[PDB]
Amino acid sequence: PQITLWQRPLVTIKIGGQLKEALLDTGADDTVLEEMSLPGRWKPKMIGGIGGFIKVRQYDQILIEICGHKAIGTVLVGPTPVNIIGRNLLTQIGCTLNF
Amino acid sequence: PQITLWQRPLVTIKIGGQLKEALLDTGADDTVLEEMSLPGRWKPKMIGGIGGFIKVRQYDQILIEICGHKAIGTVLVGPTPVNIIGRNLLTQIGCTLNF
Ligand SMILES: COC(=O)N[C@H](C(=O)NN(CCC[C@@](O)(Cc1ccccc1)C(=O)N[C@H]1c2ccccc2C[C@H]1O)Cc1ccc(Br)cc1)C(C)(C)C
């Protein structure tokens, strides 16, 4: 589909059996979601944004579904103000910027 | 043009007669650039991101070129980690997300 930017580009994602609202963020290297449980191993990571850095948990090879499009990749979990879908997953669903 | 997201969507912008590199950011509501001088008066603004909030100076009706596309709008200046082109200007150049 084609999503305009008149409003924040929020979409529904399915992950870990839960449905959540997330922001398609072309300026985000990674994907980070608010506190939640995920299966498998994880390792700590520090990520920076405007405002400074926060500590998150990194889970690899996680299945996710964005607008019906399936993909797999690394998902970060931590004290983020909003759920963010980063480029690591946007590429997998074939998302591009056009103008 | 169509921009894929395998790499950061960094483009060249022109403001105050100078060229700078900036990140096309669909997750950012506003546009914030690293410290620089701009004309006119400014108003205070707090912008929140992943690590919290930062104080910035808000300049309105500023001329800025993005990938050759001319725009005139609000530009924030402050201690941002990278120059960010937000939706306020992405909408002016007619940018959309597609997949
Ligand atoms: C590895 O680094 C990364 O990729 N980090 C990402 C990141 O922060 N990228 N920055 C883009 C900004 C991302 C963001 O859209 C997220 C966001 C959206 C909506 C609500 C809250 C937060 C945001 O902060 N938006 C705010 C904003 C920005 C400008 C003007 C007005 C506003 C209001 C908000 O919309 C750029 C960057 C920062 C630090 C570093 Br070292 C490098 C690059 C990550 C993975 C942490 C999300």
Image (cartoon, coloured by chain):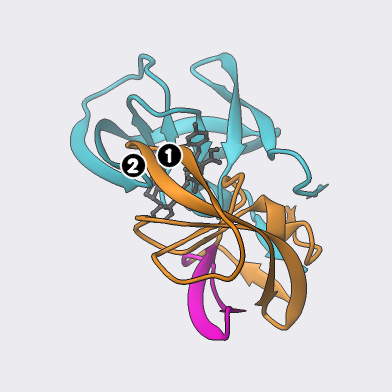
Chain colours: A orange, B cyan
Amino acid beneath label 2:
Gly
Along the viewing direction, whichever of B1 and B53 lies nearer the viewer: B53
Q: Are marks 2 and 1 on the same chain?
A: no
- Residue beneath the point at 50% across and 28% down: B82
Occupied quadrant, residue B58: top left
Q: In the shown orientation, is residue B50 left or right of residue A67? A: left
* Residue A13 colored in magenta in the image: yes
Residue corresponding to mark 2: B51
Residue A20 percent across, percent down from the top left: 49, 79
Please state the total of marks drawn on the protein image. Answer: 2
Residue corresponding to mark 1: A49
Determine whether label 2 and label 1 are within 8 Å by CB: yes
The answer to whether the beta carbon of the residue marked 1 is less than 8 Å from any atom of ligand 1 is: yes
Subunit bearing disc 1: A
- Residue beneath the point at 58% across and 30% down: B22
Packing grade of label 1 (10 A; few <14, some 14-19, many >=20) is: some
Local SS, label 2: loop
Q: Is residue B4 above or below residue A37?
A: above
Task: State the mark number for residue A39.
Answer: none
Q: Quadrant for the N terminus of chain A, please.
A: bottom right
Q: Is residue A85 above or below residue B64?
A: below
The answer to whether the beta carbon of the residue marked 2 is less than 8 Å from any atom of ligand 1 is: yes
Residue A17 percent across, percent down from the top left: 57, 86
Q: In the shown orientation, is residue B39 left or right of residue A92? A: left
Amino acid beneath label 1:
Gly
Local SS, label 1: strand
The residues colored magenta run A7-23
- Residue beneath the point at 37% across and 42% down: A54
